[PDB]
Every structure is written in structure tokens, then in C-alpha cells.
Image: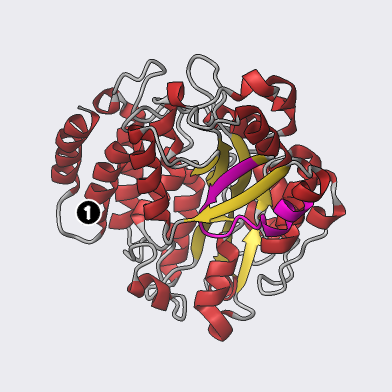
């Protein structure tokens, strides 16, 4: 009798899968643990890892946190010791890489992803003289320069609308495409020596000066309400955000949204998670086996149909369950095929160092101050550099 605990957050969609696994493996008993919030899941992770007690046998980890635990990889099972090297080709290469240490240890098996497209307001595009067919819209945005140029064209015709919701979310989209952002591959902080980072900053700041930003902080009440207005015409759009947009825009948004099979710069990803196995586990082989099964293509397809999470396993993209998916709210867009393409065109080569999230926070706070008119661009950039140096310690 192998007893395994798995700690998840939000809705991984695994409830039926646990029943299936126990039916196939009658010696294994699975118990799921759910913290009340994602922040408390993280805090439990941090607290239990440091105390040496209390961790689940499988701990879920969102990709935006995993940088902190790559630096603590000694405390996690290297899944290569349990067959990861044979499984590697199951996943998109960039999904595997984000859970791989500098020295090659693999500490997580990838669950879902958030491959990004550009969603857009076809009613606002029409009124601005832009194309509205998603195949034509896709040709407008091969790179960020073209994206902002189209935004200025839009803005010149539409004084009461902005191009995108906030400078910060545009920053997130662009920064994560750079080959390096804050760190060298040896975890050396170089944010103040990276001219491409400043060029990214300059280009977004110039967009805000051109009126392209609605200045709405993501997930704020003002941002939520703005979906029922003409406040902004485009968003960088992971697959999972479509449902958020449709909920927030509601009946006001019916007939007004579409999604284009494009992402400026090639591809982008926002979100997705991993299953990890702490060395605290007394059943690392059974834990790794269950984690591998939960993230196998057949199971990622089941999760996709249950809760809509987009698979990170390339075999799932050969399934008609995925590729036939259409989104009626978004003008019947073929989102299954679109987001397969968007996932296949993600390239991640940026190393995330031990304090990547803390450093990024000072840059996005500074950019938000510029966006909101509270600080000039040059003063905010100098302040971000000062604070990032401290954050990097």
C-alpha cells in the first residue's frame, strides 16, 4: 500500500484521473491537498521545503515560480533518475527546458501551457479602417515594431480607444522573448548591462507617449469593468485568457472579439505548471511514476476536455479533440488549430536566475508609474535599476 499525496492549486482537472490511476494500480492510494489560495500553496511550499517536513509527494509548481526552486534543485528529485530522459520528447522542448537546471537536472514534468496569440476587437478594427479577417490581421503583427505602428495607425483614427490594456502586460510579452533579460547563464545579474532590455523599455514607453495604453492594471476592478467599454482594442492572449475576456466583456462583447494566429516576435507563452517530487517524499519512484502518467498525452487530453487547459505534450496536437476546437464567442475562431500553431512557435532561450521574479517586480512597478503618469521615463528607469540591484542582492 503506497500512499501518495499530491498538492495542487486552482483546478488541475485531475479528480477523475486519480480514480483511473487507482483502478489501474490497486496498491496506490492518492490523496489530493488543496491550499485555499495560490499564495498559500506557495507559502506552504516555501515553509515545508525549509522545515524538511509536510510536503506532498507531488508538489505542483507554476512556471513563474520555478526559477526559485531550480536554485534549490538539491531538494527535488531529478526525474532523470526515474526515466525523464526517455520521456523528454513527449513535451515541447521549451516546456522541458523551463524545469531543467543549468547542470541538466529535470525537476518538473510539464502540465498545461498558455501559448499566446493576439486577440482583437473586430468592431473597433472595422471602424478604424483596419482589416478584420483574422488571416489578414495576422499579417499586421509579425514583430513588435509593426504591432506598435498598427497601434499608432489605429489611434490616429480612434481618439477614444487605446491599442492595448497596459504597458506592463506588453512588457511581460516582450521581455520574456529576449534571449537574456536579467541574468547570464551563470546566474550573474546583468540587468543594468543589457541594452536590449532598455530598448524594450524605450519602445513601450514611446507607445504610452503615443496614447497606445489604456493604463489599466491587470486584474484590477477598473481593468475588469473596461471590458464593457471601447477602452482597448488588442491583448496579448494566452489560450486560457479567452474565457476571462468573454466573462468580463459578457453580452457587450458578443460579436466584437476575434483572435489572430500570430504573435509579434514569433511566439510567446504565459503560464502553465509542472509536477515536482521533493526529496522529502518517501516514495519517489511511485511519485515520479504518477506524475509522469498525469502529464502523459492521453491524460492531458482528458484535462483539456474537462477544464480546457492547453496541453504541453506534442502528441496531443494530433488529436481531433484538440484541433477541432472552435470558440463561438470569438467569432467561431478555430482556437484548437490556432493555439497548436502558437505553442509550436514559442522559443524560450532566456535563463531565469534566483531572484528573477523579485527583479521583474521592480521593473514592472516602474513601468506602471510611467504608464500612469506618476514618474518620468528616465527617473523610473533609474529607480528600477537601483531597486533591481538590491533585489538581485
Q: Which residues are magenta?
A: 3-20
Is residue 91 visible to us here? yes
Q: How many marks?
A: 1
Residue 336: x %, y % from top left:
75, 56
> Helix or strand or loop: what does disc 1 sit on?
helix
In magenta segment, residue 9? yes
Q: Is residue 362 left or right of residue 309?
A: left
Q: In terms of image quadrants, where is residue 178?
A: top left
- Residue at 57% x, 46% y is 6
Q: In terms of image quadrants, where is residue 330?
A: bottom right
Q: In terms of image quadrants, where is residue 292?
A: top right
In magenta segment, residue 193? no
Q: Which residue is mark 1?
A: 370
Is residue 207 depicted above or below 288 in this figure?
below
Q: Is residue 159 left or right of residue 252?
A: left
Most foreground residue, 212 or 192:
192
Residue 59: x %, y % from top left:
52, 41
- Residue at 34% x, 66% y is 216
Residue furthest toward the front? 1
Is residue 140 visible to us here? no
Is residue 359 depicted above or below 138 in this figure?
above
Binning the other alpha carbons within 10 Å of mark 1 as few (below 14), some (14 to 19) or many (20 upward) gives many
Report the coloring of the rendering. secondary structure
Residue 115: x %, y % from top left:
60, 48
Most foreground residue, 223 or 30:
30
- Residue at 62% x, 81% y is 254
Most foreground residue, 226 or 84:
84
Residue 90: x %, y % from top left:
74, 32
- Residue at 56% x, 79% y is 253
Residue furthest toward the bottom? 251
Is residue 187 depicted above or below 62 in this figure?
above
Image quadrant holding the C terminus, namely: top left
Amino acid at each position: 500500500p503506497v500512499e501518495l499525496t499530491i498538492a495542487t492549486f486552482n483546478e488541475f482537472g485531475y479528480s477523475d484521473l486519480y480514480r483511473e490511476y487507482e483502478a489501474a494500480h490497486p496498491n496506490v492510494k492518492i490523496t489530493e491537498r488543496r491550499a485555499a489560495t495560490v499564495d498559500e500553496h506557495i507559502k506552504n511550499l516555501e515553509t515545508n521545503l525549509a522545515s524538511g517536513s509536510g510536503m506532498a509527494d507531488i508538489e505542483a509548481m507554476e512556471v513563474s515560480w520555478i526559477y526559485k526552486y531550480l536554485a534549490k534543485a538539491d531538494k527535488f528529485v531529478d526525474l532523470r533518475d526515474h526515466g525523464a530522459d526517455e520521456l523528454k520528447s513527449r513535451w515541447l522542448d521549451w516546456k522541458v527546458a523551463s524545469a531543467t537546471t543549468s547542470d541538466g537536472r529535470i525537476i518538473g514534468y510539464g502540465t498545461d501551457i498558455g501559448p499566446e496569440a493576439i486577440c482583437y476587437r473586430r468592431d473597433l478594427f472595422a471602424r478604424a479602417g483596419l482589416p478584420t479577417d483574422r488571416a489578414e490581421v495576422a499579417k499586421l503583427f509579425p514583430d513588435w515594431t509593426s504591432y506598435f505602428a498598427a497601434g499608432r495607425r489605429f489611434k490616429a483614427k480612434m481618439p477614444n480607444s487605446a491599442w492595448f490594456d497596459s504597458a506592463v502586460l506588453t512588457w511581460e510579452a516582450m521581455r520574456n522573448q529576449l534571449i537574456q533579460a536579467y541574468y547570464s547563464n551563470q546566474d550573474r545579474y546583468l540587468g543594468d548591462e543589457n541594452e536590449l532590455l532598455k530598448r524594450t523599455w524605450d519602445q513601450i514607453v514611446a507607445a504610452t507617449e503615443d496614447g497606445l495604453s489604456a493604463k489599466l492594471p491587470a486584474w484590477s476592478d477598473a481593468w475588469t469593468k473596461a471590458f464593457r467599454t471601447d477602452a482597448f482594442a488588442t491583448m496579448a492572449c494566452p489560450g486560457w485568457l479567452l474565457g476571462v475576456i468573454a466573462d468580463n466583456a459578457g453580452t457587450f462583447g458578443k460579436g466584437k472579439w476575434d483572435v489572430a494566429d500570430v504573435f509579434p516576435g514569433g511566439g510567446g507563452n504565459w503560464g502553465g505548471s509542472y509536477l515536482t517530487v521533493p526529496t522529502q517524499s518517501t516514495q519517489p519512484a511511485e511519485a515520479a511514476k504518477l506524475a509522469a502518467w498525469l502529464t502523459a498525452p492521453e491524460q492531458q487530453i482528458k484535462v483539456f476536455k474537462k477544464v480546457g487547459s492547453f496541453p504541453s505534450t506534442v502528441d496531443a496536437y494530433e488529436s481531433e479533440q484538440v484541433t477541432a476546437q472552435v470558440n463561438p464567442y470569438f467569432n467561431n475562431a478555430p482556437v484548437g488549430k490556432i493555439f497548436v500553431n502558437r505553442a509550436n512557435n514559442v522559443i524560450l532561450k532566456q535563463h531565469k536566475g534566483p531572484r528573477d521574479g523579485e527583479i521583474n517586480q521592480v521593473f514592472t512597478e516602474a513601468l506602471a508609474r510611467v504608464d500612469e503618469g506618476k514618474q518620468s521615463s528616465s527617473a523610473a528607469w533609474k529607480q528600477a535599476l537601483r531597486e533591481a540591484d538590491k533585489a538581485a542582492n
